[PDB]
Image (cartoon, coloured by chain):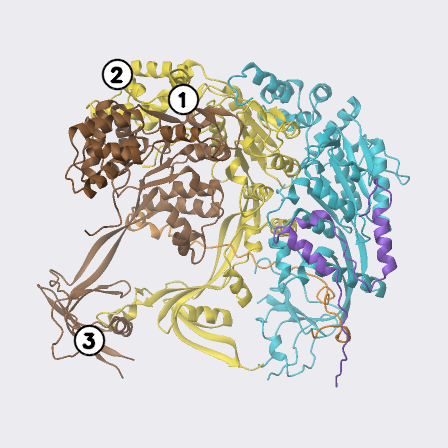
Chain colours: A purple, B yellow, C orange, D brown, E cyan
Amino acid sequence: LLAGPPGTGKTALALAIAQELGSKVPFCPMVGSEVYSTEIKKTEVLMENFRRAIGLRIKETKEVY
Amino acid sequence: TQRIASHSHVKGLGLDESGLAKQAASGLVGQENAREACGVIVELIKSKKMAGRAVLLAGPPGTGKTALALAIAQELGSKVPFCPMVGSEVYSTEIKKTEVLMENFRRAIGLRIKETKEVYEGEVTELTPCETENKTISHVIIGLKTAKGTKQLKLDPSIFESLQKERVEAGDVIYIEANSGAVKRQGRCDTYATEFDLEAEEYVPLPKGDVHKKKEIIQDVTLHDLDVANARPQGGQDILSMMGQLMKPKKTEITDKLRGEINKVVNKYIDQGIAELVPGVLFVDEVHMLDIECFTYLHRALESSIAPIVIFASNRGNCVIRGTEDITSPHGIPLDLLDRVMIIRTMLYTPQEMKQIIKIRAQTEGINISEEALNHLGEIGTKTTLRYSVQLLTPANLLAKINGKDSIEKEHVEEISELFYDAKSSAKILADQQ
Amino acid sequence: VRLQRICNHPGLVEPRHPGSSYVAGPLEYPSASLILKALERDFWKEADL
Amino acid sequence: DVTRIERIGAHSHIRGLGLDDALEPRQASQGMVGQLAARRAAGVVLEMIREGKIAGRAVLIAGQPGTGKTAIAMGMAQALGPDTPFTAIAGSEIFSLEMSKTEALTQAFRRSIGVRIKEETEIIEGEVVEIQIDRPSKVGKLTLKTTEMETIYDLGTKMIESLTKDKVQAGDVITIDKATGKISKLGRSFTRARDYDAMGSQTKFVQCPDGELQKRKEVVHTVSLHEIDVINSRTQGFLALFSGDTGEIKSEVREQINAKVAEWREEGKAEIIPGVLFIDEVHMLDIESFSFLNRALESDMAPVLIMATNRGITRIRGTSYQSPHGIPIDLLDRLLIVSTTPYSEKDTKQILRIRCEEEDVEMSEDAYTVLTRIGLETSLRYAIQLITAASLVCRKRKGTEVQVDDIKRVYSLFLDESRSTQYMKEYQDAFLFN
Amino acid sequence: DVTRIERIGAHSHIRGLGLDDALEPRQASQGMVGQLAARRAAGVVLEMIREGKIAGRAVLIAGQPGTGKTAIAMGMAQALGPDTPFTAIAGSEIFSLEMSKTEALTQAFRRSIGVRIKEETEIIEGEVVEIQIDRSKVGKLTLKTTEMETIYDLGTKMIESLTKDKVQAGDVITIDKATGKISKLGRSFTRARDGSQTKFVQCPDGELQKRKEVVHTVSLHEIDVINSRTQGFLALFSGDTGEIKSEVREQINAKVAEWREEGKAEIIPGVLFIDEVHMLDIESFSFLNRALESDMAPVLIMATNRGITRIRGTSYQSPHGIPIDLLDRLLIVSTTPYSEKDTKQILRIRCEEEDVEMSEDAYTVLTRIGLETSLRYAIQLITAASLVCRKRKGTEVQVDDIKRVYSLFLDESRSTQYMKEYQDAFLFN
């Protein structure tokens, strides 16, 4: 939890973590208001984003004539 | 004969050539100031120059707010759109409230379009496909016969499938509309009527006009019809449209892009001389049932250049606006919307006006009534309310008929008032007798 | 003569006609070709999951 | 034996209003007893319904619980008869998830208006004397007779198809629609041959038709406006008549249907049969519902509205305000109020006597006196409910009449509200969430 | 004149911001009057918009009712022009049953960012006076053109396409060299001579194969909806978009960035205008806090009058009915009430737009009424007074006509008084 007054750089530090990790690690940004969907329940939205923050890196060879 | 209703006696505003209100004319009596104001609004509507101008009829209950709004509709005539509405209708389960309001805004804008329709009709002499690989039908050849001649035509395979639709065969009479591709098999020709003693077919005569006819008509539509017809398309021939039509139809939240495109093509029709615009009136009775979201949306809607004239009606006092939970305002309406509105003041009626309206409703419903019973009903109306006094006429007439009389007398009105009680009297029973 | 025509049948003067809808035609919404090439990816970095 | 689906309900004993030809109520007739003024008023309202001239009149039945408001409603329903519509609902039924409250009330309003469609048809009806089909394009020949005449028909192909699919054979009595060749089989006049094995259903016989083989007849079909709306709402929308998926029928469809029904009325095709909508326990309606009813009652296609409620000064749902009967005074001004009074000792005794007759129960006069005093002390419905229990108790002891001891036995077994509340207050710590 | 679909409305008279090249406002120009500080601020914001470098900028226009903040926004829309997006909504419109509040704001944001694409085409044109086409199939394209005739050898494997969509003698057509499409113009008088609403052009010109570039501006929302479904483009008209998946949006952002760096596309940032933002709730404002932190975000403009007012969805109160978490992330433009001269000039402009002539005494009386009651009330009386003058066959509006209309139609201040005189008659106070 990043806590403090407004304007003290909480979001900036989170995006700094994202920059430091690099693009090859998943970083799923989210706002708390996004859980209130009309199609699915809130816990489903949370679990979907949880799965969205976990990455899988598949290696394969493509051969073609 | 048509059924009598509450406002069936209203035929117009009863104004003279100078715009002033006659004391009793066109079913309305009294209320001269509001009738003159409504006449000014009628002049505003018929000018067709303005958009989004709004009016509120405000006054106590029973003073004729709804009657004057319907009197405007009679004064305008049936050529101008008049879309009545009540504020409770915005709470739909299928679409949001603002969409309901905007749909009713578009319903009040009319459009008279000149349409040119190509039609083919005649007895099918022969019907032969033509197919080939690019395997598939390139077109179908069809011959048609009428009293004035015959002709050979080649048509799209969609119309060919729309012919196999109707089980059409040689000797059958058909009607094709080339604009939509609609096909109707009217029946079999009357030439083959004598060929059997009993046969399940239905026979029709041969057509007498030309095989191919080019006809011009004028179609009455609204902008909402154009919006809905393109939002949920229905006239296609592709398989995907047919699959989509199998879905249960529901109202959708139509976008502003579609409405802009419809405005564009309507303007093209008007510039080409094909169409004439007939902007009309939206009438929202009991706007106090709208909530603060609906009122706030009307700020933008009433400021549009496309919008119609709008007429509001409300009877509330300094009442709480719905959806705000502590904000009182006059007429149950926000101040900001009320600034955008011309208010027409409606007044209570004197006893003489009540008697005159009761007499008008009596002769409207087909009821003879003595002067004593009329005065007694006027006294009852002053004591309780106008609408209660008017409602006693038909039961009293029924009692008089049961007694063999051809006219209401005072005793029948007394008996009906004893049998049927008013809201104030019933409330007194609840409060005092308990 | 006109009154006699009316006396015979009013369709000799004012025949009834079939009601019908106003065929409007499609709207023809245009756009560019690259819009349909979105989500396309490339063979050496996609598909076969 | 033979328990049909209709068993003895709460209002099964009511079969009318028990009124004289002059609408003067009898003290006991057609299952109704007491409530003279209310029954007279209901008779006047029933005459208004029967004449059908006036549209959208509204009536409220008011009084304490157990005073026969619903009984008067079912009395009107039974006296009115089945030919005229009578749609009955509770106020809670409009709160649907499929549609809005206004849509539900619109459907309920239009269920209560009948359209008596009338058209001419030609039939061929006769006993099949002979049929022949030379199937290899098919050809055939048919012979029909009545008691008066006989005729041979050379058949067309599609008639042969219909005859073969229906498996028409000689000895049958059939009716053939001349317009479309539909066949309907009424029965047989001659037995099938007894030489044939296994096809040996005995069946029953029907007389030969009389008169001409071919006749023209008038036929009348009755449908509600809601049925016409649902059928025309969408393609294959007739299924929603049974399933109820009538979600938010578009208003333009209803306007078109009203215009077509009016022009059918002028063109001699149809007659409008306006019925009744009954809403029991109308205090469950929201303020929006009453606001919608205010304008819905002003249409010429509106039916007669009847409502029943018991509340005094009581909160309107959806608001923080209070008004008489839990109804806003906007609507109470538009309607006439019918008041039901509490019953006396003799009226209670007569109701119990009538109820015993309906349930086939014999009781002594002391039992009637005791049950009458119980009903005056606790409630009418409780005393009515004790009748069946006392009869069962008498039956299990192999008695022939219900005696005072059986009544006291069931009074001990089954408790009323007052005693149960008293005993609950004794166990007030044991009961939950006081 | 024939009535077009657009008719004269509340903000039809304003056609821009009345600013010189130095963004200094004129007293009366382009239909706008007064509000010099607010107009200058709006001009600065407009120059910020059309440069397009800075993303996610937010502005609020605040003031008393009737002070022209909505007029200022419409002037910004007119001055910006149609070449840049300008999405306008009310705050009540995001409360959809089809989608969530955040999704509605998301696609309102994305409608305000345009993607501009240029595409090259090769096209052949000719007049169909006759077709010597047999359909395998054989033909030679016996069509005409002013410079030299459109005769041209054809590949036999596809000539049926030329005869497919009812190509008939007496027409003019165009053909694509690479796509193979064919299109028609209709009953041209030069070819059809021997229908209404057909192309009435003469014989076409040019050297047959003509080069043509075409420019399309497509919003990000259009790219989202088109690629979300097999026939998703219908949802742009029907509004049957559900909640679009996030996976579609980031792929499209990546593709748009790739096109931008590759030079195949250009980004055209626009404006989202939300009038009456006090209908939004805490959830919407909280979403707007982070939606404005995207590089692909537009300029946001908001309007609300309010004072210290309750935030919807809460018991808390805040200035402008907005939380202070969002007010820190925006610049506030203040509109002041109008003077007598500005009111008179606005009435003069409105009378000109409505084509109404009035006396100077009538202007004085109407300006008195405008300050006394309200500006919008005084604007309403112009049309009614003109109608009353017309019915008496007058040429110019006089003071008597305005007094007559003032007697007939009345404002809130007098309606409330008359209501209070009959307090028991009016309901549910």
* Mark before the other along the chain sequence, 2 or 1: 2
Residue kind at label 3, given as amino acid type: Lys
Q: Can you tell which of label 2 and label 1 is closer to the viewer?
A: 1
Across and down, in percent, residue E260 comes to 83, 62
Q: Can you tell which of label 1 and label 3 is closer to the viewer?
A: 1
Across and down, in percent, residue D231 comes to 40, 53
Residue kind at label 1, given as amino acid type: Ala
**Placement of C18 over or under D383, stated as above or below:** below
Which residue corresponds to mark 2?
A: B411
* Tag 1 secondary structure: helix
Identify the subunit bearing mark 1: B
Query: Farthest bottom residue?
Result: A65
Which residue corresponds to mark 3?
A: D141
Label 1, label 3: how many angstroms apart (C-alpha)?
A: 75 Å
Q: Quadrant of residue E2?
A: top right
Label 2, label 1: how many angstroms apart (C-alpha)?
A: 22 Å
Q: Quadrant of the N terminus of chain E?
A: top right
Q: Are marks 1 and 3 in contact (CB under 8 Å)?
A: no
* Tag 2 secondary structure: helix
Q: Quadrant of residue D173?
A: bottom left
* Viewer-side residue, E308 vs B8: E308
For the point 45% across and 48% down, the residue is D253
For the point 73% across and 46% down, the residue is E287
**Placement of E108 over or under D11, stated as above or below:** below
10 Å neighbourhood of mark 3: few (<14), some, or many (≥20)?
A: some
Which residue corresponds to mark 1?
A: B423
Residue kind at label 2, given as amino acid type: Glu
Label 3, label 2: how many angstroms apart (C-alpha)?
A: 75 Å
* Tag 3 secondary structure: strand
